[PDB]
Length: 259
Ligand SMILES: O=C1NCCc2[nH]c(-c3ccnc(-c4cnc5ccccc5c4)c3)cc21
Image (cartoon, rainbow, N blue to C red):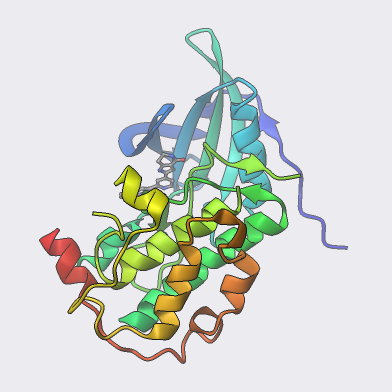
């Protein structure tokens, strides 16, 4: 009987339990994401502040429900406090030092696969509990530590929605796969997207498998109704047998330096 705990919205001042700094870890609709410190443990965390409305109350829900998945930024506590006489919801999540996915890169196929593979699990988890993330841009994929065995983790649930939408998550997955392999988006716009107008031009892509190209093409189908389901993405070999992919090298770092 493996029951994880429910969600507890603490009412004590958050300042009773953490020291809040002004280092800013991220920007978003609701203002800044602040680095804060657990007093008892002197460990570091990210703080997100929402105005308490029912939208806020819906993020926190989904995220919290989503949190017990290893590839999704984990919520550690949630408070309701007053701020300038306004109810707010404070989310305290795990702090992810490694910074944004791509930035790390700018410093191998197979390495690419592993990433896609982990991002897959994030979606797979979400989809199986009926949550569509929507906003799976690469800004929202952060690493736990600069240490190069760090884990890639998805964040930012400002646009999460219940599905009791998913096909558009797989789009992002395809765009992110794209940019991982060549170094730029498939779109160099509003009109080229609706059409499904994009190349695998060379010598950037000349070395890349038709196995891989197919897959991307299936993720970037203009028509949602048969873009690939996450369940199939994860079953597809490139991702499925992750480590037996050829360690064939790619220019992605160079290009994202150049660009
Ligand atoms: O929900 C969000 N929306 C807006 C952007 C954002 N960043 C975060 C976030 C969450 C956890 N950690 C970070 C983070 C931690 N450490 C960093 C070090 C250096 C650069 C960026 C960092 C980001 C950011 C959450 C959100």
